[PDB]
Length: 56
Length: 243
Image (cartoon, rainbow over all chains, first blue to last red; front, side):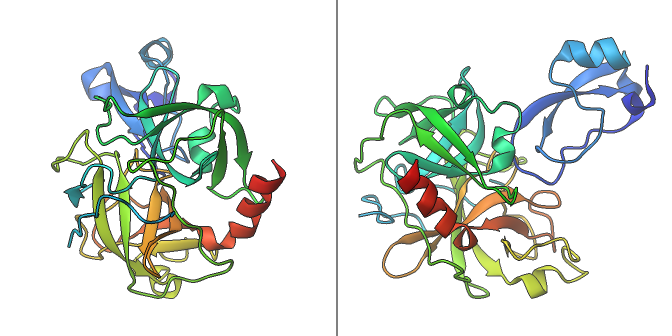
């Protein structure tokens, strides 16, 4: 599990509503979050599987 | 007549704000996936054209992957009288700003629930503290109106003040305008992107901004940043007439 799996969910400054997934270390689960559309971090996945296969 | 709704809009003195009167913002568009989930706003500026933000079209350049919903009040339970039109063409603004044009696969029918908005003067600057309206089905953040068209009456904040360290600190460009209450609590949010920032000017509503970004939603001293439309009018005209 790469380092960025430990980074927090960054929606970003933009103000699109892209539902996405981030890995949650303290819960050891892939949870849903809104991505704003610009900037942010690698802890950002489009499927629940992509999060799990990468950071879980 | 564009910019003139046949249902008189509420004035409300989207996080915070109020649920709008149905069809009082007839130019409001819900941009969607083929699945049909709302992820962005849009603005009917003419029967075949919708103005939005470029970040909404990030993933795919396929125009057929985009769907335009017109005359809605509910984000999910669409009214029976609603218009669902596919996008024919996308036009990203060349200097890579957060503004884009969607050409509709078929022109929208202008009714009393679907009316377009008016374009501002080229290089026009909305004066500081001008009260404009923000509409959209974005996040509400624990505030009422989730799933319904929400509106907010926000004052324009001039960029010299908006770029003060206390606020956005040099983040805001010439081709952007700031808007909102500095005390926070009322603002556009994720899901409102591409949405209209309209200003009542002559005797009708005029599109002056496009919901772009902000440092968080509805936070104190953190006004929303909007694409300054008046800077792209000339570009918009030439796209509509040549395409």
